[PDB]
Amino acid sequence: KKYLQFVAALTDVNTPDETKLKMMQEVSENFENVTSSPQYSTFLEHIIPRFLTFLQDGELQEKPAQQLRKLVLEIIHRIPTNEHLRPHTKNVLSVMFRFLETENEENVLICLRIIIELHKQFRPPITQEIHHFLDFVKQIYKELPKVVNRYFENTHSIIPRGSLSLKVLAELPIIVVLMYQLYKLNIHNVVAEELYADFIAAQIKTLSFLAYIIRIYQELVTKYSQQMVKGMLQLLSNCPAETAHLRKELLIAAKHILTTELRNQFIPCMDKLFDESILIGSGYTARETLRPLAYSTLADLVHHVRQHLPLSDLSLAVQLFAKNIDDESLPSSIQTMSCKLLLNLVDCIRSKSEQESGNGRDVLMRMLEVFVLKFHTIARYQLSAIFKKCKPQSDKEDKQTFQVTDCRSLVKTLVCGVKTITWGITSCKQFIPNKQLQPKETQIYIKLVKYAMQALDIYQVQIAGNGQTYIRVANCQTVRMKEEKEVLEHFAGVFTMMNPLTFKEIFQTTVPYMVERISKNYALQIVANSFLANPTTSALFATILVEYLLDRLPEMGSNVELSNLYLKLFKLVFGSVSLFA
Amino acid sequence: LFMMEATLNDPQWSRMFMSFLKHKDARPLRDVLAANPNRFITLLLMRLDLQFQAIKIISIIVKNDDSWLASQHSLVSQLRRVWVSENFQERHRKENMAATNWKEPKLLAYCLLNYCKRNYGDIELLFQLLRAFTGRFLCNMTFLKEYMEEEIPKNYSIAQKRALFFRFVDFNDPNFGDELKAKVLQHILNPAFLYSFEKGEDNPESITSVFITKVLDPEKQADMLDSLRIYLLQYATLLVEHAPHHIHDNNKNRNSKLRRLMTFAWPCLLSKACVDPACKYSGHLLLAHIIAKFAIHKKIVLQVFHSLLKAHAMEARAIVRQAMAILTPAVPARMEDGHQMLTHWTRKIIVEEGHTVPQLVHILHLIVQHFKVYYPVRHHLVQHMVSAMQRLGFTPSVTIEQRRLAVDLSEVVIKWELQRIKDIDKQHTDTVVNFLIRVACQVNDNTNTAGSPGEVLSRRCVNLLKTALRPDMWPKSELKLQWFDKLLMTVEQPNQVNYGNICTGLEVLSFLLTVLQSPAILSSFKP
């Protein structure tokens, strides 16, 4: 019935307003109702002449032209098959070329949508008309400068559609030389700059253009246009902050460009690399939820290119990063990535300290300060957060488990970074090997050990087979799955390498807290074992421990816990004496 | 001997004096300083380090005393002065690579908080936000944030909530003298509402004042609101939600159609303006909350529903999901005479999606999936979602969204059939079962051979299949002979012999149980 119903309703101009909408409803019903093979192709063969005669007439308008374009968009939505796709191609590419880059309606948008949905069939012989479309693309891209240069202070959605259409139409077919012409267009790209909303629309047109220029992350091309990409990066900083989705897509396109070696080496020499995590790569005052992606991109960039940055660049980079390392609103994953970046950059700063009279000691100490501050903050808050929900004597809990794991990895990354930093300040600024630390960094290290002996307590929480967290026992004499053994071994290594008579003061001041935490956390006993096993540091630590325990001997008769702790400590002391007689 | 500027500027003697005053037996040393607060005034102004030294000593004194607060008005008159001074902010922000005096802000904020917690100074308490969320943050955030989050909404407004809110509103005048935009004016909305909610579970004049004082686009100047708009919308939402109910709201909201909340939210979220998704969707949520409790207007609820459905394009997930959770049960209850009407409007907006807008379709599918309980009476609308799931599962769902959404949408119809039988299009249900059979044994290959997630969802899909056969929908299920053959015959090709066949074996075992219930399948085991 659909056939004879849609055919009998044939009406050109006798009823322009509502008859076309009724036929649109009828064809929508036809599309929602299944059609058989005998009622499949003839429908389209009849629709095509109808679409032709309806587009022949009626080229901010709200006239029957609108419902005509809507009927066309529905015929597009059909997507029945491909056999009858040839004349529709001609009609579409004929209606595409005219009345573009002007105050035209969305007719061209649905036109590019059907063009995209059309080339999926891989039609060889239609490459000539799409080649003419690419010639029109050449025209409009070269015309863009004049367009923005004619509209001054005294729509705009066609370029993104055309760009994404050309992208999806150049990705599927055989690789041809037309992409090199599109590259030459990227050389002629526009780089200069409610009507302000239209200018921002032009900015996002340029952003979509760049998104198409992402091809720089593909087969190599002759890149002799650094000035154009620099101007585009400037426009990016000039882009609006209210649009979150477009800014996110732009940051993605940027990080994709920065994901190749031949493009990274040209970034640091641009504006002295001052355009880092300062409020350029993120919304100025609108939104900062996409901050993780920008921070990860910047971290990867600075990591790949750290070997070519002077003192000022790395100093201000650390200044900008230490600010976000402490941000509680960011997920702990970003904090771990920033700690990794800092501990990987510490070695580069140390190696570069030979130049420009050094000046690295100050920055290294100032970032060791933020490292110990993060240690203290996590030992103060993360430990409490987990202890306030432990199930003694054993969904949001699934995510709390992942958070606990992120904290368990954060403590390890912090320990490793602190070790690498201790290796740093003791090997730069002339320089004298094993220089005695000054009182400032000595007290900083005292507080560092005092706060890290607590952060290491995160390894006393376990995950059960039902999802609920479980608090570990006080003492079980196990291996702890080997996860934390290396962590506290590196924690001890941090101190095994420093000056002997500074170790002496640090541990003479912190030995009571050490035994206290060991009694409250038996896993820390290996720290003393590592101190006693490392040469050049076992004698001092053993002497301090015995001098502290000889006065606390009567305390072994009161309770059994501290008595056993002191017994194990004396056993370790005797083992060390046997090893370092 | 230590307070001599010549010796007080030296780092060595200054550190020595700090360590001495920090000692436990420094009681008499602290008293001689508490007896002369004017001394610090001469230091709290190249000799700029004396400011930091004085701020450090004051912090030690405050920490060791905890009561020398009411006698230091003349001191805080200069301590707060440097806190709010733009010179301090700039000097400490511009260059902070390796600059000394790094802990000055933390101690300054600490002593300011210690002073303001003994006497309730509104201007000082609100100016404290200069480093609570905005400004500079190096260990300075949490110490004050946790206080304002837990201690403030515990005993602060136990007696004068209304007067305190009026003072915080009158703060606009002194605030505009030094801070004109969200950077402070937006943060002041948090300290008040933690208590407003803690005690929201009493202040009528404040409800009337907030509406008229903060007229739509306050001061008739929309250009200055960037983030304050979102927090004001959240204020209005949680206000119409908990603290003032109809009893207190209807008194002044009778003029909703006027400059009141309704016009404060509707024109911005309706028009294409306010491209910022946050403010637009927060206004949508405010309208949803208003509709949920009162304001039964001339069918504008359907307009809001449509604007929400068509607008959740890319990243509106959280806010639109909350707005639907708050509004989805409101429209049908208050549209009894238009149940069929709203359902047909939903169908319309669904069929007008011929572009298929993959992300929009996924968002709509998730929306209709969350509310399983509100579409049992519209079985007519199952064909569209079933046909959409069929094509969703066929796409290369390397991403997490498509096929997981498809399998949970299949679980949706499973539960629908469960509640229908134990209080449907037969061919489409058979196709749904065949799809659950196919997708269940197809996701096993999406993940690598081993050492990766993706198997728990396959197991839960197998459980869904096991459970879907207990209802009386099993008799017409079709055997996927060709799919099973192709997948398990892969073993003939030693490449790609992953456990996918093992899940296919478990599914063949489930169908073996089915034939154990109905031996008719014996004739269908030929393949």
Image (tube, helix red, strand yellow):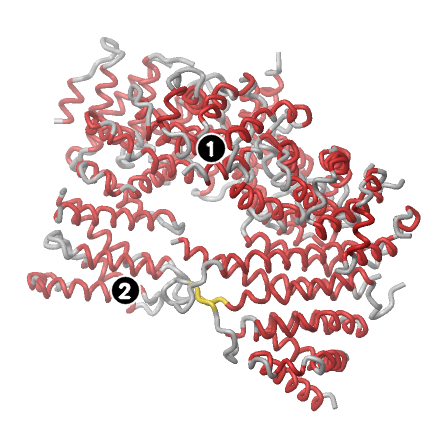
Q: Observer-nearest residue: A452 or A563?
A: A563
Q: Residue at x 41, y 57 (%)?
A: A398
Q: Between disc 2 and disc 1, whose residue precedes?
A: 1
Mark 1, secondary structure of its residue: helix
- Image side of residue A69 versus residue B162, left or right: left
- Image side of residue A577 versus residue A561, left or right: right
Tell me if mark 2 has few (under 14), some (14-19) or many (20+) residues whose alpha carbon lies within 10 angstroms of its own: many
Q: Observer-nearest residue: A32 or A144?
A: A32
Residue extending furthest toward the right: B6
Relative to A438, is A534 above or below?
below
Q: Residue at x 44, y 28 (%)?
A: B283
Q: Observer-nearest residue: B215 or B397?
A: B215
The residue mark sitting in front, 2 or 1, is: 1
Relative to A401, is B173 above or below?
above
- Image side of residue A444 versus residue A390, left or right: right
Asked which quadrant contains residue B43, the reply is: top right
x, y percent for residue A108: 42, 24
Q: Chain of mark 1?
A: B
Q: Residue at x 40, y 69 (%)?
A: A393
Q: Mark 2 = which residue?
A: B503
Residue B306 seen: no
x, y percent for residue B488: 26, 65
Relative to B104, is B173 above or below?
above
Q: Mark 1 = which residue?
A: B234
Q: Are marks 2 and 1 on the same chain?
A: yes
Type of the residue with mark 1: Gln
Asked which quadrant contains residue A241, the reply is: top right
Asked which quadrant contains residue B270, the reply is: top left
Q: Residue at x 13, y 42 (%)?
A: B424
Give the Cα distance between marks 2 and 1.
48 Å
Tell me if mark 1 has few (under 14), some (14-19) or many (20+) residues whose alpha carbon lies within 10 angstroms of its own: some
Type of the residue with mark 2: Cys
